[PDB]
Amino acid sequence: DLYSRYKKLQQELEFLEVQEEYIKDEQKNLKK
Amino acid sequence: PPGGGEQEPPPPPAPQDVEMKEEAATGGGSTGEADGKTAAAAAEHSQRELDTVTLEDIKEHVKQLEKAVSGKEPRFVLRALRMLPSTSRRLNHYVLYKAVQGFFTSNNATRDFLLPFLEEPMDTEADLQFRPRTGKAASTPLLPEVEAYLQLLVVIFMMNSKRYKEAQKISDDLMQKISTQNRRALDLVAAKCYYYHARVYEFLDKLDVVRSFLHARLRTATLRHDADGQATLLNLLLRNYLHYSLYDQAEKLVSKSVFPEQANNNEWARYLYYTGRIKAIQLEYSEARRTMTNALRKAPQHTAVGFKQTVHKLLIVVELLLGEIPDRLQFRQPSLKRSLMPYFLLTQAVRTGNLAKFNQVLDQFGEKFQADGTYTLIIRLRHNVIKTGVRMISLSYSRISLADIAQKLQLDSPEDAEFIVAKAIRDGVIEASINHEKGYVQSKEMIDIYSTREPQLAFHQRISFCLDIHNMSVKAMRFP
Amino acid sequence: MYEQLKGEWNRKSPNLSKCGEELGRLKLVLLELNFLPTTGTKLTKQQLILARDILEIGAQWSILRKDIPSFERYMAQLKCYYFDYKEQLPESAYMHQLLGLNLLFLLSQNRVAEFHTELERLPAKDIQTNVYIKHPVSLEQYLMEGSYNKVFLAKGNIPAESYTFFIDILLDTIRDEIAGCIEKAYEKILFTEATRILFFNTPKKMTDYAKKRGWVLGPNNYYSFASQQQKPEDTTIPSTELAKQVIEYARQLEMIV
Amino acid sequence: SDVNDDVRRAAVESLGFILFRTPEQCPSVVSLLSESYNPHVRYGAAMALGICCAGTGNKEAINLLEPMTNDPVNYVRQGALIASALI
Amino acid sequence: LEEGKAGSGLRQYYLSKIEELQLIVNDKSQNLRRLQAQRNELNAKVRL
Amino acid sequence: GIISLLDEDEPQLKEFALHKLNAVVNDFWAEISESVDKIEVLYEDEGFRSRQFAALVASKVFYHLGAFEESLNYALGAGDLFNVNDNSEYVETIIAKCIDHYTKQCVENADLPEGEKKPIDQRLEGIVNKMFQRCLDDHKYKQAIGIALETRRLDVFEKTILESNDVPGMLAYSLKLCMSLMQNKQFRNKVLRVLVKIYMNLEKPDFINVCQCLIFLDDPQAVSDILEKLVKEDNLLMAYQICFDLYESASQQF
Amino acid sequence: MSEKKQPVDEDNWDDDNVEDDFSNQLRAELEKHGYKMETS
């Protein structure tokens, strides 16, 4: 289980980072 | 018994009940927070921690007969807590041992049965799941055992309780650390026993094995993450070595570890005190006093506790070595009454150009100066008294001769007056110049600073600092 | 074992084979046992009685033979041997002189920060008695007051031997600072100002300063060059960093929402 | 960043085509995009939530589409009915 | 030891590595939900 | 007192100094800051027989400071007196950085299969397999298969799946990990085609495993090479099953 | 809130500033301050 979780924590980290960019990206563009 | 025995039934029953309920719902609240949503940064962990330092040290100091705190060990001796029927059976026991000790008496402590009250509650099918429950029930006997102060086969029961706690501490930190992380309480719990581990040795001898173990905990911490463990462990290594009147200043100088990054507004206050002491003794005064100020002005929410007395006592000393001195007795205290008089008598004779009253006060108040904990005033003040005169004159007179300043400074030598000012210009007391032709000593020339690139550079300090105040205060609040 | 306890030390020491003998004597002590645990057991305190003493006479040799890296070696090794946890270690009569030799050495190397932070080990031997520590701390006091005369009037008053290599560096670290203080916007002074700023009636020192530096004696008048600055500032030239500061403001004003 | 509503729909309808294998990510991004200011970003999030999760009782996508079908705008009510039938 | 000489060379490579992958996600959840609510405020302004 | 001993040119003295250095390094931490510079400048002496402990205490100080690459360069250059240590808190972290450094090198070199490869030290792979031999000593090969997938190596993959394996059913477990958690498509056929190596010379050939992999791969003739053998062996009860599984799973143009 | 470090721990209204400035400078202010004219 110690190898199976470690990629899963990467996938949750990578899925988070595209989101938190995009919500910073949208809220920059939402001001117009 | 007619007067004092009638006020024996009221104190146990309700403080037995209401103190038991608060720690139960917190420990039940900590367990559910440990099980789900480990993001417990703004949870009840710190405020329960702020209760145990304050209330349980002022509510009770003795082991509380009629089974009040003494009944906690025969209550918690039969605790297993593994499965859902096993927890419901123990929750049946929690009700029953309170109901028996509330109605009748169960098992009494006679200040000697400390080994049966610590090994059998540690045993009896106890698991390593409920870790703060185990760490709290070992830390709470440590307070009345020290506050009793009887010293009759007690140090060894302090010592074994510490070593068992450290054995439970290492068993947490190495085996099954999956989302528990009790370091937020374990640092202070380590700090509290180490205060007792220092004091008990301080009754008899020095302490060095405590510090070698403290390196070892610092060796086994600090690689994971700095989560205010390393901050307090750095201070506990630092406090004894400054308390030793030998050395270890250079060990703190090379100590490249200044990054605790948060302190719950508790550690960084006293962390900035100790590094102010060391920059003061290493003759770096400007950075010393500005962080001595930053320590004092941080947390004044303290009703005459003593470190506030001690930073204020030192800050006026490092101000006198610089030269300026504001009011200090303006916030008078019933504890300040024995400390406000010698330093005010000190700064009186310093700022004046007198010596015999100064030596008389120095001869009278040296016993306090040793009891405070600074000895370097004997060498660093005689530079101040001789330079207080030349700084005041150079501030006053725009152009004074050497033969006048020699007679004004009761010096009786018109030859070293060039040498004093040459020391004054070199040391940075005042910016002047000596015309070595007949004794012209001039001073500053221009006063325009405004259109000469002064103000913008301070303004760039003001903008960049307050926008950093802004953005940190932005991120610290939108948590939901 | 028990090799050359008191050889050529009580009278003279012109030779140098005693150096390698003491070196091999230091090889024997380290190969006996380590000094690192040091719990009790007066048997191993006996070998620490001798091991401190052979460094003391080794330090007396290094200060007799004019050797700078040696004296700091033996002193720090002795300072490690006073650095003992379980130090019962009965009273050595040379420790007061040994610390006085270290304290004046550290003052000679211009370490005023190291000077004071050393002065924590002595509880009440600074004022009450012990001239061997009282003489450097009175000396530091005289540097802070401003009496260069009281330094050299007290140079001819030594309790133990002469402290010659200490006062030679003490002469050395004063006179260059005096020379560093005078090489300024001054132009010329007569011999009498260098007889007041400096000292003795026509020594080789004015010839020493004439060959090394300037201060060339002409018609009874020295000549010091001006060591001031002449930089013609305009200061609207660093206008790029100002526009850099204006832009990075509005960068930090915007760009994060 | 783009301004035509058609490409803004077709970009946020493409969420289901790229994340159908992991249903634990489609309601994370739709639940905020289905509450935009225009209906078009709200609409294409509703079609993406339907085409991502095929036939699994989710109870969250159901919970998100319930204010989606409760909307004044007619077509964003429509695709919410489409997505509720698809799940 | 079939396990005690194995928990510090090959399992400890995994346990000491997952912790950073856990705590960044635990930290960036706050930073995400910060950006979430801030987006919910401005969207509540524009719609109104 | 060791500092002047490190200054004095004597080989029996310098051995005794570093013998005192590596024993007390738990206590004096930044006191030896200038000396480990003097050890490292005097490390290029190849005719001086104390260089292993010289690279040891140079490694011990920079990890304390935080210089991890210089700790890792001198951990490799130390040698076998480094390699003997397995039971420590110090040794377990720098090998964790070493496996970190080794797999991020192999991830880097997997993008240029046409030469231009970075040089590989033999001592870094000498603790890769030594740790992998400790992985086999665990009697736990899920631990061993994890590094073997991270290191981007194929023969260690084939050796772990067939060694002892109680119970021998890890061929499906590796196939799930390759299918479920994966980002790169480059070596994904390599992991697939090394699975069909162990599937074809398996003691129970051939039907379900290879055909489901070759549906996932793009072999139009290798399926016909084995389906003819399924007919030639007179087996048509499960050949009837494997062809419907080929019809249901695989798409057009296959 | 105690912090586990305690070793040990009216006549005017507010007059420190004048007394830090002037403590003992002949506050009768008549005998030299008014009597310079005999001296000059």
Image (cartoon, coloured by chain):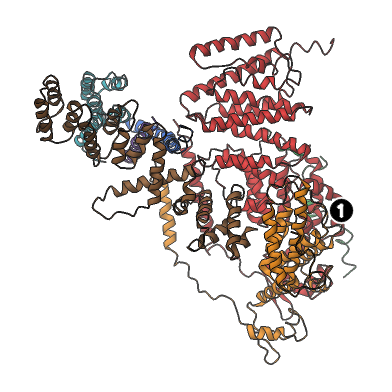
Residue at point 84%, 53% (across, down): B362
State the hue of chain D. cyan
User: In the rendered view, would you say C233 is above or below C30?
Assistant: below
Query: Can you identify the residue that label 1 sits on?
Result: B363
Left or right, B84 with reference to B387: left
User: In the rendered view, would you say B61 is above or below F102?
Assistant: above
**Does residue B424 appear anywhere in the picture?**
no
**Does residue B393 appear anywhere in the picture?**
yes
Q: Position of residue D22 (x, y in %)?
A: 28, 29
The residue nearer to you, when weighing F154 against F185, is: F154
Q: Position of residue D12 (x, y in %)?
A: 24, 33
Instruction: Give the quadrant of the N terminus of chain B.
Output: top right
Q: Which chain is green?
A: G
Q: Chain of mark 1?
A: B
State the hue of chain E. blue
Q: Which chain is red?
A: B
- Disc 1 is placed on an element classified as helix
State the hue of chain C. orange
State the hue of chain F. brown
The residue nearer to you, when weighing F152 against B166, is: F152
Residue at point 83%, 50% (across, down): B366
Left or right, B324 with reference to F99: right
Task: Tell me which corner region of the image, top left, top right, bottom left or bottom right, holds residue F130.
Answer: top left
Q: Position of residue C95 (x, y in %)?
A: 79, 59
